[PDB]
Length: 4
Length: 4
Length: 123
Length: 123
Ligand SMILES: CSc1ncc(Cl)c(Nc2ccc3c(c2)CC(=O)N3)n1
Ligand SMILES: CSc1ncc(Cl)c(Nc2ccc3c(c2)CC(=O)N3)n1
Ligand SMILES: [Cl-]
Ligand SMILES: [Cl-]
Ligand SMILES: [Cl-]
Ligand SMILES: [Cl-]
Image (cartoon, rainbow over all chains, first blue to last red; front, side, top):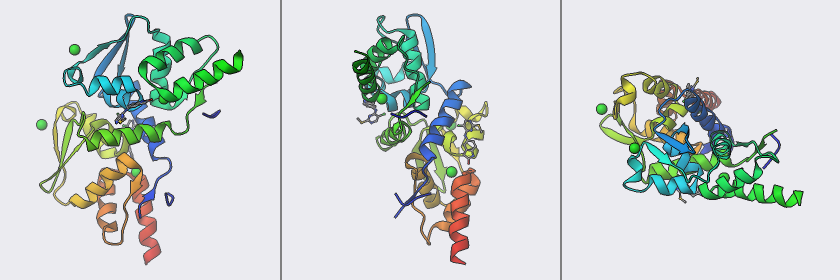
């Protein structure tokens, strides 16, 4: 999971 | 396009 | 000896979401506490272990309406349906418990994992 | 303020290809010079400008069989159908002309672009  |  | 187009999977999913937003070729209605959500059976199966099991069943594969367990929160479902079609999860302090419970029921293992991690960080 | 799961689009496409290989919920047969290819209308639309136009048509959206132009090579189509479901293109000296012609007909702009580039490199 990432900060888009 | 890339070499997978 | 194939070549690979990096953005292809993302572009396919973006187009599938465009079809969903315009209600094109949607073939099922998911009912959650009287709220109704239109979707593509194939996308639901591709994202959820529960929908995969439902639509591979010889009788249920032909149903145009699926009713979820009454304990399922419609907002939690809406957030997960948006995630299925976009890879983006709108996870907030106010919805994390409903989102985790819905993801556990839908059998969306990666969503369950991030919810567990975010909850553990807050304790 | 969403979080994003990097591998989600790739995982969805991988599962859609698993459904195709097991012939699960395929809803159309594409006929190419007597060869028949089963697929999901939504995936075809998501990858091709031609299929997008066909299945948004109020009459054609209901067809279970689509016949392509007799000039279309079945091998070129098979390579492109595999690309649609995997992001991998099996581009070879022996098939590049048939693949480019099929991609131009199917309106798959990124495939047409790589074929033009690979052909230009060989001259
Ligand atoms: C297992 S083979 C397979 N073949 C095709 C499909 Cl459409 C599919 N979907 C599916 C099954 C289980 C799970 C998910 C999707 C997401 C998750 O967390 N668990 N699986
Ligand atoms: C344009 S809006 C839109 N909405 C939904 C879908 Cl399913 C769609 N597909 C599509 C249209 C045109 C093209 C492709 C896909 C690939 C390509 O090269 N050209 N387009
Ligand atoms: Cl029904
Ligand atoms: Cl998931
Ligand atoms: Cl027909
Ligand atoms: Cl393309």
